[PDB]
Length: 220
Length: 188
Length: 213
Image 1 (cartoon, chains in turn purple, blue, green):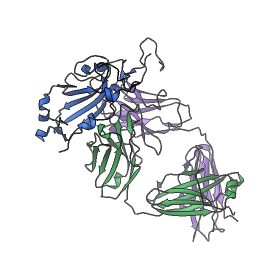
Image 2: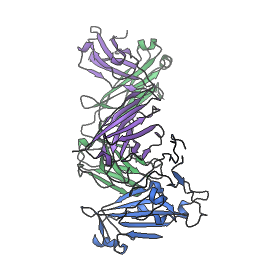
Image 3: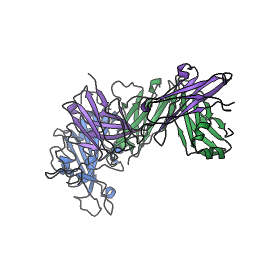
Image 4: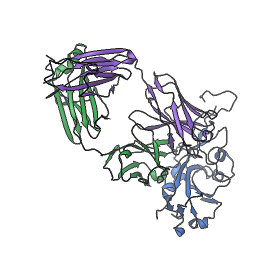
């Protein structure tokens, strides 16, 4: 066979909450290898989290996660665990379960990594977006919609109920310091069509069950 | 033709604590063993320039003078059992030397630590850097000290030779069914 | 703490060789391991013990260690070598024993440079009546995916209220980004104009909007 690490248990949790990640291992004798967790904050580097001995008698932890995270394994069921408590907004990252080499010392290098599970800690609750028309100004003209202050992802944007597709550029959102998301979608249309064509952007935010159909018109 | 980086290991400005020893692999270089206790096991050091190995592992740490004899196959003690244990079939050399000038400050160098407590002995070449509070009684400690497993040496220049810091480098000579990459200059 | 210093980014042409360095105090005293993380992928070990490649890694990947600098060399660079590369060591004097470097983004220049297209949108009337003002700057169709966005009130730089994305691949294989400037309607009206300054490969495109609305 070949090595295989499949993490699960990620999601979104409020600060000071708790979460448990599980890593299912196959393709190697799970009872003989030291197991670790390595996380990566979004747009950031790799930070070592914790590790465990082949039997579970020895557990190591990073200074940041000491006293809050506890790592355990069940060699009978070939599973690694990472119980997370008192979660902070700095704990948001993609957590990989990794496999050490065969032998001692444990912690030199990590040749096998899992696919990765995402853990997001945010104080933000579910909020519908505020949609504002981006009016064109004075052969093509640009108009669009500003989808501001919504949580969580995703929001789908279409134009004229999908009848207008050419020239539509919907941008990836921003995660503001407030923890809320915002994005804009702009469509380039012929200048002559302004005044004689009505453009409506359709914003759907399923998590808040909010559909907004904002009409964009030239500013007088 | 590449020289083995022995001085990079030996002349490292900072050595690790014995509970957190640093291991470096030496490979694909000619081994001039000519670039204090010098104990070798399972090998003749007058033939060290006269041998080839697949890989050479270089472990480094710091202990007292009295603990140097513990760095050897079959030894017992707080260092051998809980901090650094060699296999009974160890092949290689152990080198230590006085380091009171480098690792002893007047007030005391408390950055160096050793493991006093553990629930099991260290299996050959194992390492343990955990801070888990040792439970000596019948009641679980619940993470609050129930003794801290590490103790600082506190190296001052005024200590005796049996308590002065010593820098130890453990060269492990290893053979496998693979081409030899570390050889003395006489078989390069 | 043992800190591993890596160059933030390195750009190389296809077929040439790229060099990614890893710096540290007496880095020759430690064994350096290299990891490759392709976009959207997990880290993969490509070099261990400073010279050795695991099974499956091509011979184009090479490692080296000397003094205070350890380098990873990739010869005959291909498009699939575009990834984040991390060097890793172990230290016993640091209290953080597993050390990962800052990482290097290796950019392969497989497609020619494209200047960005910038659209700046002033705050809408609707938003202004809601006691809010947002400046939207949309950047598109630029290669490589690296842009610097600066906001100027009249002619003075603005740093507070700026929120900028990271470049993302579009359908047409180019990159796009958006930057948002947050102001109250009072600051928006009190200035004669606001500018969105986009720098890309030494060339700058600036768009300006005015509160005359």
